[PDB]
Amino acid sequence: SMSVKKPKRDDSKDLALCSMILTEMETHEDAWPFLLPVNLKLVPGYKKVIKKPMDFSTIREKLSSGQYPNLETFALDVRLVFDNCETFNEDDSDIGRAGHNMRKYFEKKWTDTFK
């Protein structure tokens, strides 16, 4: 409350560390469905169904231009990529499995870096 604060967690490395995680997600062999925005002209249904499209290249641009206020808003966009994937793709598809694999990969790096 006013003039009463928990001890200050060092967030000075968070930008660099999110960048490193994102590099590791970009270079994973199963990243290919997520590297670029889904083409809304060429994928029927996507525009209407997926209200907030997100992909690794958009996260990279937001990260590089100071559009994440804190490390949690960064994690919310990464998770949005996988939530969108599950919304649109069957679990038993190459893309559906890719999304599950990457969400696991992310969540481990996230816990190991920050928790």
Image: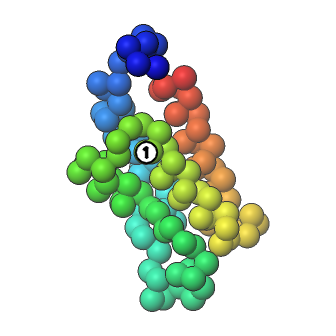
- Outermost right residue: 92
- Outermost front residue: 2
The quarter of the picture where residue 92 lies is bottom right
The kind of residue on which mark 1 rests is: Phe
At horizontal 52% and vertical 81% (from top left) the residue drawn is: 47
Q: Is residue 13 above or below residue 49?
A: above
Q: Residues within 10 Å of mark 1 (few under 14, many from 20)?
A: some
Horizontally, residue 102 falls left or right of residue 6, namely right
Q: Is residue 28 above or below residue 39?
A: above
Using the rendered image of the protein, determine whether residue 46 is visible from the camera's viewpoint. Answer: yes
The quarter of the picture where residue 8 lies is top left
Q: Nearer the viewer, residue 28 or 52?
A: 52
- Outermost left residue: 65
At horizontal 44% and vertical 80% (from top left) the residue drawn is: 39
Q: Is residue 11 above or below residue 5?
A: below
At horizontal 29% and vertical 56% (from top left) the residue drawn is: 61
Q: State the residue position of label 1.
A: 74
The quarter of the picture where residue 17 lies is top left
Q: Position of residue 88 (x, y in %)?
A: 65, 72
Q: Position of residue 51 (x, y in %)?
A: 54, 72
Q: Position of residue 108 (x, y in %)?
A: 58, 34
At mark 1, the secondary structure is helix
Horizontally, residue 47 falls left or right of residue 23, namely right
Horizontally, residue 98 falls left or right of residue 112, namely right
At horizontal 47% and vertical 26% (from top left) the residue drawn is: 113
The image's colour scheme reads: rainbow
What count of labels does the image hold?
Answer: 1
The quarter of the picture where the C terminus appears is top right
Q: Position of residue 55 (x, y in %)?
A: 44, 62
Using the rendered image of the protein, determine whether residue 20 is visible from the camera's viewpoint. Answer: no
